[PDB]
Length: 192
Ligand SMILES: CCC(=O)N[C@@H](Cc1nc2ccc(C(C)C)cc2s1)C(=O)N[C@H](CNC(=O)CCN1CCOCC1)C1CCCCC1
Image (cartoon, rainbow, N blue to C red):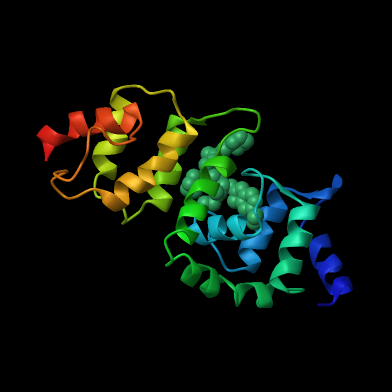
């Protein structure tokens, strides 16, 4: 890996007002160079591989360490990696890691939980086509005005989505389910 080539590539994205950070324009540019829409799951997958702390933020350390471990000193080398990252998420567990990372990436730094409509946005993206009851779930949350989602409720929603049946017949009340998922089963059962 040519470090000089990687340092100049970083210079293309860095904030004109802060050398140690990539700004909103630099994040947009990086997506454009990767031929990616900024609302694509592939942008979230890249954030996951670069292990970015929070959304709308990208540091020098994250970019440099990310590209080094991937062995990319160019955009074309990184674009060649995107189908390899998508393939790796076919593995449950790699997807569990990615899904759980999404909570920490989306929430505000300093805050322990994720705001409801922010969690719904990301659920719509990451649980797209892999949670039958997503429509009812969002409806239930927006209706019973739950302000924020706790880490364990977000995390156990994946366990719920992979274990639950179409009729919810295999759901166990005595199971280690958070009150929100448990209340959702009470609300949803008459509707299916
Ligand atoms: C789907 C991609 C994604 O998460 N996009 C984020 C913005 C990004 N931040 C980073 C940071 C680093 C990197 C590196 C390349 C690794 C990439 C990105 S893309 C977003 O707009 N996320 C929105 C929600 N956010 C918002 O609506 C704005 C949130 N505010 C911004 C100001 O500070 C407080 C939080 C999405 C839109 C798409 C569907 C899901 C909800």
